[PDB]
Amino acid sequence: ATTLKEAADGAGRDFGFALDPNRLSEAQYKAIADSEFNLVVAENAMKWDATEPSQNSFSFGAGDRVASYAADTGKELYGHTLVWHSQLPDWAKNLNGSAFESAMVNHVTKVADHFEGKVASWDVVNEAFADGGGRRQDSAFQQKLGNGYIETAFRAARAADPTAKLCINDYNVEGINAKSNSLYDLVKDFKARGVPLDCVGFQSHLIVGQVPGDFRQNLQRFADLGVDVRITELDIRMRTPSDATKLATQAADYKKVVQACMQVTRCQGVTVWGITDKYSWVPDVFPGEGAALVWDASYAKKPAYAAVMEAFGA
Ligand SMILES: O[C@@H]1[C@@H](O)[C@H](S[C@@H]2CO[C@@H](S[C@@H]3CO[C@@H](S[C@@H]4CO[C@@H](S[C@@H]5CO[C@@H](O)[C@H](O)[C@H]5O)[C@H](O)[C@H]4O)[C@H](O)[C@H]3O)[C@H](O)[C@H]2O)OC[C@H]1O
């Protein structure tokens, strides 16, 4: 393998990235996008704010640009995300009861129908659970609709798109803990009752030096419920600026995560949350943290690059 794309291809797995379609006009970004990945997800372009800015009025230009990019370069297209408490427009937050449920169902239906036959898998529901266990405590969906909204979203997604793989996605669920246990209970329940659900995403927003040692075991127990598993938003952030020690640890951490996936037969692959540190979400949310991705801010391969290639068995 001369690229991460080749390494993942050879491993029979996906290696993806989070795309900002506006950055496609930056040729270096596009070069790496084109050559290093076999899967793409919209970083923002297919979220509710980006697709339904007013009630039942849709803005698919940006999402279409992502879908077209995937089709033009022969990459799998992963959909993110139909139902999520964040990046939810004020008009939706202002609705209540059945009016709110209807806006959710309509959102799921229209977006899934629009991308049907293009998007292969959806994050139907994103970040439904709470650190420490149970349901998320600051969600419009949880508050207005209660426990049943997850099942409602999945069934609506399947009604719109009979064949797309329908995933639930979350973070801080990589290890076995109260959060991943709650997620596990739901997945088992849905499979038991025949609720449409095909996959589970593990965001893997990790901190350098802190990869859960039970990650493989956790992925395996989910896979054994009869669903596929995927690492969906991998980045491994550090205190900036980087140095040799931090970059070495980060490389080892990337290797650990990719190996965990390689060790689980139903782990579809790994998607990193961006290409270059230049554009990563991390520094804006975590002051003084960053350098979380595989390429630095000048597009140089970091040691993480070799680690990923090695982990895919290249
Ligand atoms: O106006 C919009 C504008 O909002 C966007 S900016 C956009 C914001 O969304 C991000 S994607 C981002 C990916 O991470 C997930 S999970 C995230 C993780 O961090 C937690 S703290 C957590 C605690 O425990 C630690 O050990 C663990 O490692 C930590 O991660 C945080 O609370 C949680 O939210 C996140 O939810 C999600 O927002 C995009 O990349 C940005 O671009 O741009 C478009 C504009 O129109």
Image (spheres, grey):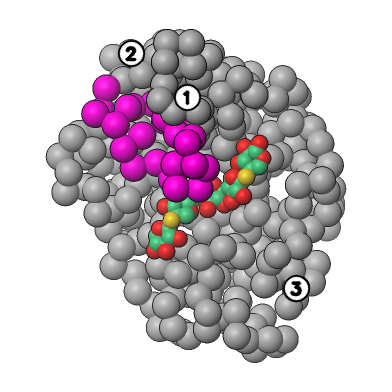
SS of the residue under disc 1: loop
Across and down, in percent, residue 200 comes to 65, 44
Q: Earlier in the sequence, mark 1 or mark 3?
A: 1
State whether label 3 is within 8 Å of ligand 1.
no
Q: Quadrant of residue 258?
A: top right
State left or right for residue 40 relative to residue 262. left
Q: Marks 1 and 2: in contact by CB < 8 Å?
A: no
Residue behind mark 3: 143
State whether label 1 is within 8 Å of ligand 1.
no
CA–CA distance in space, label 2 to label 1? 13 Å
Q: Is residue 19 above or below residue 62?
A: above
- For the C terminus, the image quarter is top left
**What residue is drawn where x is 80% and y is 67%?**
147
The span shown in magenta is: 277-300
**What residue is drawn where x is 56% and y is 24%?**
208
SS of the residue under disc 2: loop
Is label 2 or label 3 in front? 3
Is label 1 or label 3 in front? 3
State whether label 2 is within 8 Å of ligand 1.
no
Residue behind mark 2: 1
Residue behind mark 1: 12
Q: Earlier in the sequence, mark 2 or mark 1?
A: 2
CA–CA distance in space, label 1 to label 3? 41 Å
Across and down, in percent, residue 171 comes to 64, 43
**What residue is drawn where x is 49% and y is 16%?**
246
Tell whether position 280 is magenta.
Answer: yes
67 or 138: nearer the viewer? 138
